[PDB]
Amino acid sequence: ERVPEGSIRVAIASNNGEQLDGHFGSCLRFLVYQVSAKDASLVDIRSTLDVALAEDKNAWRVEQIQDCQVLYVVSIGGPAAAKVVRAGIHPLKKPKGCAAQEAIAELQTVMAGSPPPWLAKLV
């Protein structure tokens, strides 16, 4: 899908259900949500299984979320984060972990309030 205007794609690093409990470098999959200031929907679940076959692992991981504008992790290495950033994705962390829904809700408070220009343009 070509995201609909007014919305963005959000990747969440995860190992269980719809939890934001994964570390970038070792997560089982990326939950991908379509999020607007007011609405959010789970659109894809991208498994990281095939990273086992990659020689350039961080590059591969980022490739799985190349269409996301934001990425949530519990944690992420410096180098990994640089690649995430180089891809134009904004990495956000939640060191203690939480429900994907809670992170998205938080992200929406920004979108709905005073989003920075980059985000405002989107939404």
Image (cartoon, helix red, strand yellow):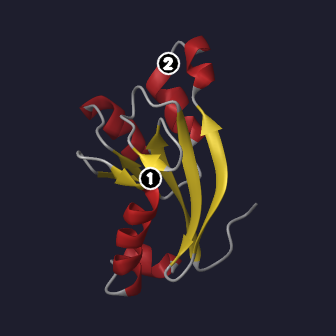
Q: Measured from the top left, where is residue 8 in percent x and y? A: 55, 67
Q: Residue at x 54, y 42 (%)?
A: 30
Q: Nearer the viewer, residue 59 or 48?
A: 48
Q: Residue furthest front?
A: 17
Q: Is residue 2 above or below residue 99?
A: below
Residue at the limit of the structure toward the right, as seen here: 1
Which of the 4 image quadrants contains residue 24? top left
What residue appears at the point 34 percent right and 53 percent down from the top-left corner? 98
Decide if residue 53 is on the left or right side of residue 104. right
| Kind of residue indicated by mark 1 | Gly
Instruction: Work out how far the residue at label 1 is from the one at label 2, CA to CA, in angstroms.
Output: 19 Å
The answer to which quarter of the image holds residue 46 is: top right
Q: Are marks 1 and 2 in contact (CB under 8 Å)?
A: no
Rendered location of residue 59, percent (x, y): 49, 29
In this rendering, the answer to whether 13 lies above or below 35 is above
Residue at horizontal 41%, vertical 71%?
105
> Where's the N terminus, which quadrant?
bottom right
Q: Secondary structure at mark 1?
A: loop
Q: Which residue position holds label 2? A: 56
Q: Earlier in the sequence, mark 1 or mark 2?
A: 2
Rendered location of residue 80, percent (x, y)? 35, 32
Classed neighbour count for the residue bearing mark 2: other residues with Cα under 10 Å, few (<14), some (14–19), many (≥20): few
Local crowd size for mark 1, using a 10 Å CA cut-off: few (<14), some (14–19), many (≥20): some
Q: Amino acid at mark 2?
A: Asp
Which residue is at 43% across, 52% downward? 89
Q: Is residue 9 above or below residue 17?
A: below
Camera-nearest residue between 54 and 24: 24
Q: How many marks?
A: 2
As drawn, the label of residue 88 is 1
**Quick one: SS at disc 2?**
loop
Task: Name the disc covering residue 107, or none.
Answer: none
Q: Picture quarter containing residue 90?
A: bottom left
